[PDB]
Length: 420
Image 1 (cartoon, rainbow, N blue to C red):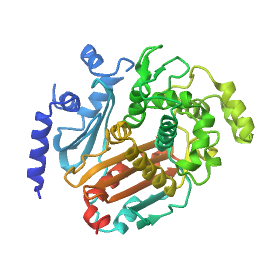
Image 2 (cartoon, one colour):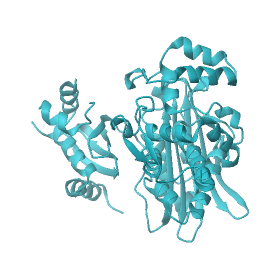
Image 3 (cartoon, rainbow, N blue to C red):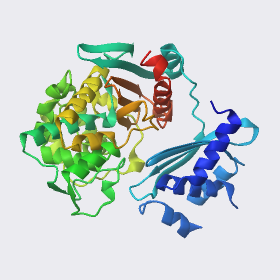
Image 4 (cartoon, rainbow, N blue to C red):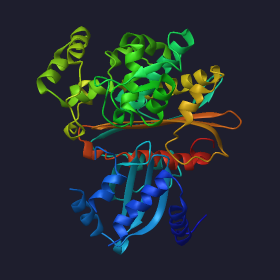
């Protein structure tokens, strides 16, 4: 086990050596903090990207020492110590060519090493937040429950819904009504907000179903998801939900696009009240009328609307079922297309000597955070972990590093918590 000094030194050296998009960005960002220029900033950020003031304020909190460095593909975190033992985390999210989309410096998210499931529960519990932890081992003869808190509660899950959209897509591929190499076309009407990168492509951009689905999962690409949902059609997605593993499809009817959640959730307040008072028919009618180019921007987001049904609600059993179903879907697809999409982004640094495959999905909306993994070892033993939080106030949940970090610690302690 590396001692504190060893660990910090290893992180510092790894940051310096990391020849990757994340390494480049993390070093540049750290340079902003440790150094003493508008065009250089412009070149490092997404083209649609106050900042000088933000950097002045960050710098006022140093000097900083790198204590940990956690690059994970397009997302990365650097743990910093400032004077007097105060710690911060620098968080980076990149686009597909390594341009910075999000850069934040925030008080450290503290997660202890976990020994028991009660450590997880007592760490996670936050007054005003509903949470759920569900962990199982998949077997021939059903699931062995390792730990459960409120798995039966249906909760909003944000982009977990893209797991159902993936199963719907695979079902249509198997039927031969859609193909992996079929071309989808981005239009102004199909463009959604981030998470994702496909929104930054020009109008008329032609992309395969394969690459669109890949980004839908690996980047949680909302525009990719909406492109797939448009191609398949809402009714086709909704008719798939029962078989895909959802216990009460009516909770996700009409099955919303991300564009619809954004536009309805944070646009016209009257239109949102009409949703609340309407039945399924009136809601479908409202959505059809709402079709068009988005008016809502990222800056408009904030207030919670999941409690109005403007999200995607499922219980923990539903998540386990969709993941187990996807594992089955992947196995049946001898081309490996499904597998490539599902395993592209595991959301953490994975011990590949232990885990042969890992599926991962995150979801987040104001007042909503969730992470789930399927992890299968080289013998073929699979575990599923489902973490969920919901609140009426987004500040009670935060940016998701807490819930994901709790996931990371469970997986680090798999020998105690999953495979004991």
